Amino acid sequence: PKNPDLRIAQLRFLLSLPEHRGDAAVRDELMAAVRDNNMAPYYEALCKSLDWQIDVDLLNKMKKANEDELKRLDEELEDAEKNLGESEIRDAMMAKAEIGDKEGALTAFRKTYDKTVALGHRLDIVFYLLRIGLFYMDNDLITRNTEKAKSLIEEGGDWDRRNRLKVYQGLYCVAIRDFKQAAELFLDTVSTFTSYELMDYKTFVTYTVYVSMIALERPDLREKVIKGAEILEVLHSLPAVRQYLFSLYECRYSVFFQSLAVVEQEMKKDWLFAPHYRYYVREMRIHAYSQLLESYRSLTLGYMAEAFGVGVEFIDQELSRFIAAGRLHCKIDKVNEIVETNRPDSKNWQYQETIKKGDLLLNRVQKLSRVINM
Amino acid sequence: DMEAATGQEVELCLECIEWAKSEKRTFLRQALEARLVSLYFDTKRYQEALHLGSQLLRELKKMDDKALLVEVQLLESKTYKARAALTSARTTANA
Amino acid sequence: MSEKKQPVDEDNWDDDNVEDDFSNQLRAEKHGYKMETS
Amino acid sequence: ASGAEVKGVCTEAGMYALVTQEDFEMAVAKVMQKDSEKNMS
C-alpha cells in the first residue's frame, strides 16, 4: 500500500525541495497525522518544516496511540508465536511494523529478514523496503532490498510480481540518471496497470517519458511511444509531453523550447531530481541540434533562430559552452553562421579505438606482466 | 436531450440515486447508474467515470441480469486494455 | 605500498562532475523571458 | 477424466480468454460435448 505512502514521500520532497511555504509541508504532514496514525510525518515536519505550530499534544496523543499500537504489536509477537506460525508471526509483525518513529522500522526489519521464508515473506519485504527508501530520496534501501530479493524473492516468482520488481528497478533507473534501463524495465505496459506500488499509472507515464525521450532513439522512440499505443490509451491523459514527443519526431524546435521550459520547471518541482535534473534539458538541446545540423551543412543558426525563438545569442553562448563541453562535432560561426554534417566514425575513430584500447590494455597487461618477474 | 445545461443534469441524477439508496430498487438504480456514467463520458470525466464503472460492475456480474452487462462493458471500452475489455464484452454478448 | 615521504599526510554524485561542468551555465526564466525580448 | 485433462481444460479455458470459471466451463464444453444427443433416454 505504498501509493498513499508514495504521496507521503512526495510530501517529504515538498518539505525538502520547495521551502516556499513551509506550512504547506506542515499542512499535509498534520493532515496525514490526524488520521492513519502517521506520526513519522509529524516528526518529519517538526524537523525540516515548521516546528509544529500547534502539534505539541494534538499529535502526541496519536503518538501515544502509535505507542500502544507498537506495544500491542510486540505483545502479539509473543502471543502468536505462542502458537505455531510458519514465520507468519514475524511476518505479521514486520508488516504491521512497516507509522510512528523508526521504532516501527527497527521492529519491522529486525523481525522479517531473520525468518523471511518464502517468496512473499520477501516479496512484501522488498516492496516495503522500496517504500521506506522512497519516503526519502534513498537508493541504499530501494536497491539493497532488491539485492536481498535476488537472494530471496523471485526464484521463479509470479508472471505478475516479478514484473513489479523489475518496474521497481526501472523506477530507480529513472530516479537516477540511468537514462535507459528505466524504460527498458518500464517496457512492460501489460503488467503495471494499477498496484499498491503504482502511486499513479499517470505518474508511471511521467517517470516513463522522463526516461524514454532519452533512451528511445528515433526508432525506439516511435517503437515505444507511437507503435506502443498501449501507453497511448492512457497517456491520452497527459497530452503536453505527449505532443512534445510528437514534435520530437518532426523536430519542431520552437515548441521544443516551449515544452522544454515547461518540463524544466516540472523537473525543478518533481521528486528524486532536485540535485541532478540539470543535464536532461541541455541534453535534449544538444541532441536535437545534432540531427538538425545533420540535415545538411550550408545552413545557419539564424534560419533556426526562428525555431530557437530569438536564439542567436542564446545558442551563441549555449553551443559555445556545449562544444566547450565537448559535444556534437559540427561547424558554426557568427560572421558566417555555419552549419555542418561531419564526424564519420569510419574516418579515423572507428580505426582509432583500435589503439585507444590495444594500448590501454596493452600496457595494462604489460605492467601486469612486468611484476610477474619484476 | 434538450440542451447542454450542465447545472442540473448530473445533480438531479445523483438525487434519485440517493432516493434509490432510500428505497432500494435494484433495476431502477441500475437504470440510473448506466446513464450517469454515459453522462460522465459526455464531458469525458477522467477517473470518476471509470470509478463508477468499477463500483457497479462489482455487483453486475455478481447479480442475475445479463443484458445491461454487455453495454457497460462496452461503454468502458470507449473510455479505456480496451482490446481486453472488448473481448470480454464479446463472450458475454452471445447469450 | 606507500614507502615515501607521503606518509606525512551517485544520486547526484554521479551527475556531480557534470554539475560542476554545469556550474557555469545559467544554473537553472531568462531563457523563457528571451522569448518576449523580441 | 484421464488425469491431465484438468490441464487441457485449463488450455481450452485460457484460449477462450485469449481465467474466469466460465473459461473452464467453455473449456469442458469443447472437451465434454459428445457426450451429447439425447432423445434416447
Image (cartoon, rainbow, N blue to C red):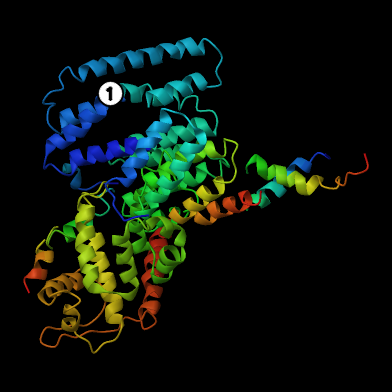
Which residue is outermost to the left? C37
**What quarter of the picture does the N terminus of chain A occupy?**
top left
In depth, the one of A241 and D23 nearer the eye is: D23
In depth, the one of A173 and B16 nearer the eye is: B16
x 82%, y 47%: residue: D33
**What quarter of the picture does the C terminus of chain A occupy?**
bottom left
x 76%, y 46%: residue: D29
**Residue C29 appears in the rendering:** yes
Amino acid residing under circle 1: Asp
Compared to A180, does A76 lie above or below?
Answer: above
Q: In the structure shown, which secondary structural element does the residue marked by tag 1 occupy?
A: loop
Compared to B14, does A322 lie above or below?
Answer: below
**Place of residue A177 in the rendered image (x, y in percent of width and height, measured from the top left):** 31, 54
**Residue A374 appears in the rendering:** no
Compared to B51, does A184 lie above or below?
Answer: below
x 71%, y 42%: residue: D25
Which residue is outermost to the right? D40
Report the chain holding disc 1. A
x 40%, y 16%: residue: A73
**Place of residue B90 in the rendered image (x, y in percent of width and height, measured from the top left):** 60, 54
**Place of residue A247 in the rendered image (x, y in percent of width and height, measured from the top left):** 31, 71
In depth, the one of A100 and A306 nearer the eye is: A306
Compared to B82, does A292 lie above or below?
Answer: below
Q: Is residue B47 left or right of residue A41?
A: right
Q: Is residue A281 left or right of residue B9?
A: left
Q: Which residue is mark 1?
A: A101
Q: Quadrant of residue A104?
A: top left
